[PDB]
Image (cartoon, rainbow over all chains, first blue to last red; front, top):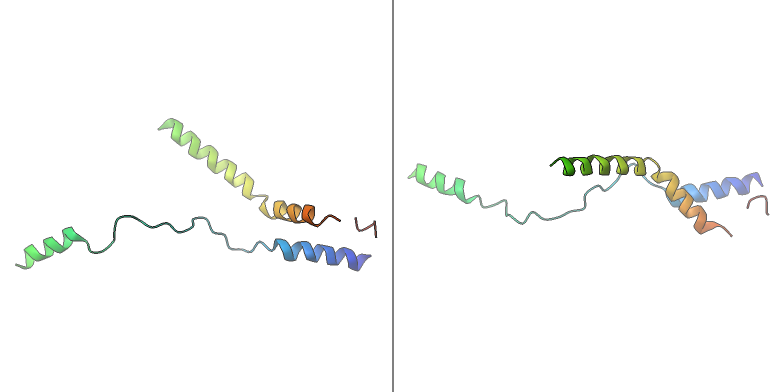
Length: 49
Length: 41
């Protein structure tokens, strides 16, 4: 009976198994592109010219 | 802005207290799903 209780506890622990890792924010895409950066490109062009 | 900040603070408080029992809550959920010698029961 002690081994049965231990096996049940191990079943609970195996099934729950919440690890030390958690997903707080799932991925979403920023609708504004990060490249090309138009303003810095045009400023670089003007200054280079 | 004060209403929004009150809502943010209360949401954070509720989320924290909810997470501080997540492992036990999942264990209880699986125990409920696992409920069917009678000493084990």
